Image 1 (tube, rainbow, N blue to C red):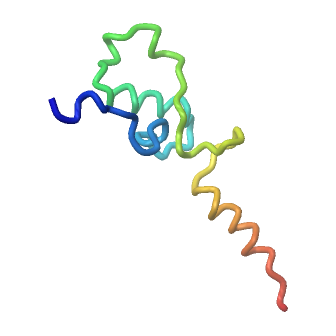
Image 2 (image 1 turned 180 degrees about the vertical axis):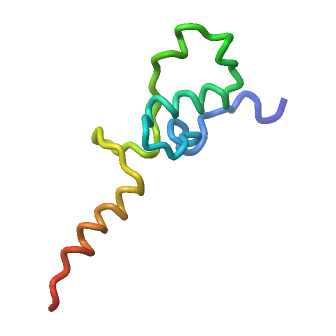
Length: 84
């Protein structure tokens, strides 16, 4: 069968289906990945209560961020511009 043996994880595979949530990003991205995989939450018992997945709203440091890092670093750099 074509395109069947060479299945690899796609682009940004931990942080593809991560929804933009600021409440609990690791708790919500694990649930959005749980239903995108097709697994019903009633079929899984305690395996779906406490779990975490990499979200796009969390940096490499443990800090929940709204917009990305390059335009959060740019917020500090655009505010720190004295008149030349």
